[PDB]
Image (cartoon, coloured by chain):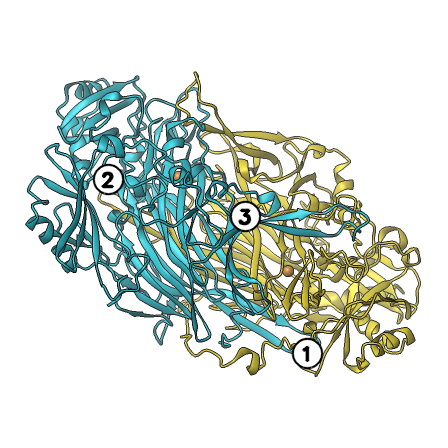
Chain colours: A yellow, B cyan
Amino acid sequence: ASPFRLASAGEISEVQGILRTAGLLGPEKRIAYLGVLDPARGAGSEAEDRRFRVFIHDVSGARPQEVTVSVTNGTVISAVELDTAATGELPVLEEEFEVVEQLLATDERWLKALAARNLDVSKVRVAPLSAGVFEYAEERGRRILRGLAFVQDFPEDSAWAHPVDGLVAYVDVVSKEVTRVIDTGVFPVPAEHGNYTDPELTGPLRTTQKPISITQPEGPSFTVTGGNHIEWEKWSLDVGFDVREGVVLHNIAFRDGDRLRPIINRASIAEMVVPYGDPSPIRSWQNYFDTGEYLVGQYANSLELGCDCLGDITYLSPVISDAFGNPREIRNGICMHEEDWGILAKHSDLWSGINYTRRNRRMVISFFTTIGNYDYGFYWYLYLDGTIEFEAKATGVVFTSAFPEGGSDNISQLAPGLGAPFHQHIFSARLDMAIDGFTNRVEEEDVVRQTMGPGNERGNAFSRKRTVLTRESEAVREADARTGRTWIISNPESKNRLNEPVGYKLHAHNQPTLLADPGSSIARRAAFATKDLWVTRYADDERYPTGDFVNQHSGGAGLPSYIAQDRDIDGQDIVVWHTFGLTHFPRVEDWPIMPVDTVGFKLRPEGFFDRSPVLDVPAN
Amino acid sequence: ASPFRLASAGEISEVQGILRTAGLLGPEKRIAYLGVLDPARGAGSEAEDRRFRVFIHDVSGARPQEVTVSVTNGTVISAVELDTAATGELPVLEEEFEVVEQLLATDERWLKALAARNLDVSKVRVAPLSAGVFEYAEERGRRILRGLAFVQDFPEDSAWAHPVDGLVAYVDVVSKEVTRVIDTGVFPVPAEHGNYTDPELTGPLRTTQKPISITQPEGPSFTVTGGNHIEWEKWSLDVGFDVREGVVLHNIAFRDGDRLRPIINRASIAEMVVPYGDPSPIRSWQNYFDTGEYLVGQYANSLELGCDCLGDITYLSPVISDAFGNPREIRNGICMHEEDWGILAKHSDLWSGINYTRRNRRMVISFFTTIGNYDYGFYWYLYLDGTIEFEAKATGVVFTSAFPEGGSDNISQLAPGLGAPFHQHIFSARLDMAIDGFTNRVEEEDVVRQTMGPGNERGNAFSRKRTVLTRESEAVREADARTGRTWIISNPESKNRLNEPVGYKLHAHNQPTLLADPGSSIARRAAFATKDLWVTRYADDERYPTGDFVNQHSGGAGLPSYIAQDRDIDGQDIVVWHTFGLTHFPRVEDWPIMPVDTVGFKLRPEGFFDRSPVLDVPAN
Ligand SMILES: [Cu+2]
Ligand SMILES: [Cu+2]
């Protein structure tokens, strides 16, 4: 069995057993995070040592713990007591979400706030949001959550269409107490509904759509062995799954005639922040670290055939651990299918009289996650020509507020009295590079313009420049669309038939990076968001852009600290961290339900192969 | 019958008849261009005056003519004698392409050049390329073409794999004479074949691909009436076709509940240049104006089912005029079909317990054109959410040269001794805007960053700015990815329910624009390529970025001259000219047959509708 196989229900149970037997999982203990560790770099051993990292939270206030367990040997390898006031709080627990609404329901100053608005508490939903690190000294070391109210006229009503502005409440989820209730003033609560399923808003459903049937009479072209190993059109890879990172890709290799060539050792979305541009004290603290604080994989939806995934679909049902160590299965949490991608190559030659056309195809691996109001779709695509692409589809319900009577520079109006604060959706991709092996380097490519003159000039010439990033301190780069800036990851010790280093080029979308002031709190906690690309020397403990504990933790602990080591990255075991996001100024068309918008990046072969890798594709 | 219907064979014949009867189409006359004129702005008349513009070339050296004909009345409206030395030569004729190879075959200094390379003339193909405007005074007023040689080992051999560097020949196609033969020196002619159909290069064709069947058991959701009027999912438009511009789109409107709302009056790719960055005297003159000089529509391929277009396809067979006025039909020259586009909107709400998912779809209208070595696919997409997108797929065979022994800064090596000069593929989209009517304006939107401070600052706030482009002189804009710059075309006199101007936002890819030195020849002839966006006040005679006669014409005559009028564009009949291209540094993977690369832009509703326009889409 492959050491990259998905964690099974049985292994989860074993971890529960081991932690219990060791006296680490008492009735007052809760599992905040549990996931397999990747095999060590020197995995040249038959030692199928299947390890698990666990974060244990204590419900009675005692110190939490980080624990590494070996399911293979049946023992606990290590256990360290965490000082959350220093390194950050553990990820938020699902069972804590309910608590904020329940506590506030009997808080006297909260009830007074609702009475001043003539709102019935039974109809007030409270969005349990992560608390960053701000000016509240009494929050340090404590497990705090922030709540924002939304009115729900009836059980099936879209509470998001009725935000209760001017009111916030901070809650201590462990000692079960309300530390603060802030009321800046009453704001009319938007009355218009936002129910996209109500036939009065949708009107008569259109009957003009004829069905589109996509089928594969002979099954798919890809094969799945060992539960998660995929083999598709020369592509070879292992589809993993982590509750924090979500779908992870291991050992991406291309079968270049007899020789299986590695390209990327491990690919994943290591982090994703959602900063809000509203300066009002009611939401200025709002910044979700979906991956870091909520754990994307935890909230993965169960995808349905025909609706979420169309065509010949093959599902993967990843196994996750609940708060007590019991295995929980995300049924159909991962969709896999290949799809037609139009024309791959084409040419009608006059001289030779030959007409040549070839269709392209892509392998799709996706999953969807729901975090409160937002829904994200993570898509990984592998193309016949050796291209790799990632794409995020952001949908759901936009986070709302009240639209001030005098208008606003940081909020869009969606309906009468209804507003939506400006925000960004910034992602961080962690590419553990293995271009034909682990001896890689990163080159930054710029288009260079030439002046008309003595040396070859009719004013038509233009070139390209390539500077090698040698040390970590100079591997923090910005995008530059004007000069068509791209980054090439190559292997200096592996050459193509023209005697040039094989490589892969990274094409970024060049969307704006983190817009917040450089001195802001979010700028610190999410410094990775301020630059388009970072390259680091590999290290087993350097897993996330922000660090291991993002919840209520001050920033710096991630990329900015890793980089300070100033290690050599010229032909070494390296890691590429790419920052890409969406600056969203909500428009009327986003209400009441937001249509999909996208972002991403792609990697294309750059002298990797000796000639077109698709000369052998057949003809329909 | 609609005044936007495709030109028929019968109308072409009528134009032939009328020109003949008027003594304008003698045996020595040839039609260089023929196409319907769009109905006048004040088309409030029942006057179905079907007019045609014609460019008549004289084979014996006499002056050419521009002629406007009325097929409805059966008369010639106007005929003017053209001074090609002033306004430019007519587009290249197909029958002229053969002439350059035939003339050179018996030229003594050409034969000497081939003998010095031990090349047999019968195996030497000559690529008939357009001659720009350079330092040759004897070319002015004359119809000249430039030829580059390529060896073809056998009838079905890829001549492109064997360029004959260091040799060029200028030819006068009307007086049938060779004006010059330049030999800068012998270069070894690359011997390796580039035959992508040869089983020795392709190896055994892979058998791993399983079929993907896309069908619509109940037919498509769109309907075609009047030969070219399309009605699909609230979208309404007329698909036109011009030999110069190719597929053109007229009257793009959206049915917003009872009210048919215009968005774009006329959309087309008004021009596309392909400048080469090689400074060598053998190719420094190379710049194809595919649309302007060769007429894209003329070389449209006949698309085949299953290969070029997959699914339930509906074809359009546009009619074109040959050089003698006879109707020529491009069979299956236009593909039209709708296709699934994944998730449109989705949300699993915790509070309401409602799970909502909707699939997106796109209407595809495409055509492919082959010009020598290059093959281009033009795709127009209409999405359910009101989004409009254009996409160009560039494929074919890369233009080759010899790779110098010492290497080069402007040429990539693809094979031993084989090179490919650096180049760009720059397109110009002409959007005749009609956002809810002809009273439109253009606003440039920039993301503005705010400093942490006294006024609302925790350093998290960010805004957006919008400057209105009022006059033509200030409507020449550059892209700015850093600030997320976009352009909004709105109607000041048409507001949405929130009392804000309805609009559409333009999202550009932000790829580098024309790289050539600002003082170069190509910079002048293709000045439109130096800026990302231009807005002009509409005018019946301002049809192309470069002008009506691009062939051997000096530049300026297009956009830079139109703009000098400095007309008011704030709430007027306006035209948006968007520049977008691909900077191509050939890689090993592009040889011998180039896999598809893409570019484009998209327009998304920006407060156009009162709420999400897709609330009425059904559920699978
Ligand atoms: Cu958003
Ligand atoms: Cu190209």
What residue type is disc 1 on? Ser
Q: Position of residue A4 (x, y in %)?
A: 64, 55
Residue at image mark 3: A253
Host chain of mark 1: B
Left or right of residue B410, residue B248 in this image: left
Q: In this rendering, does residue A8 appear at all?
A: no
What residue type is disc 2 on? Pro
Q: Quadrant of residue B529?
A: top left
Closer to the chain start, of discs 2 and 1, is 2
Residue beneath the point at 28% across and 56% down:
B38
Name the residue nearer the viewer: B253 or B541: B541
Residue beneath the point at 76% across and 59% down:
A286
**Circle 1 SS class:** loop
In the rendered image, the quadrant that contains the N terminus of chain A is bottom right
Q: In this rendering, does residue A134 appear at all?
A: yes
Residue at image mark 1: B352
Q: Are marks 2 and 1 in contact (CB under 8 Å)?
A: no
Q: Position of residue A437 (x, y in %)?
A: 59, 40
In this rendering, is residue B31 above or below A368? above
For the residues marked 2 and 3, what is the alpha-carbon distance in whole angstroms?
49 Å
